[PDB]
Image (cartoon, rainbow, N blue to C red):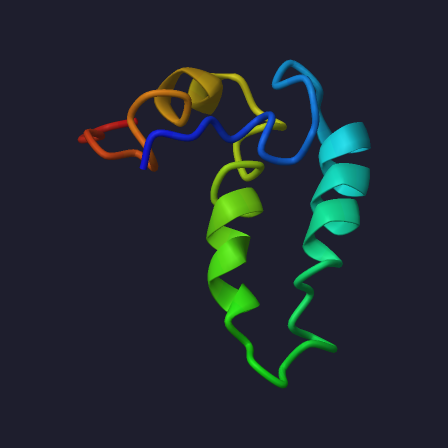
Length: 77
């Protein structure tokens, strides 16, 4: 559980959707269960890009997601 997430999709972290939209699809394709339901084990990989790249478009999360995993500690965020 010690792996970055902005780079997990070969990106820049400061990017936005432009790369997270070609990186999320370019790297998830390798797992895109929509077609790869023969195993569906990719369903979790989404937690690798969709859980990581989910904040690669915003900034307030870039500070939360880059260290507090996924809103780990958030009462009124």
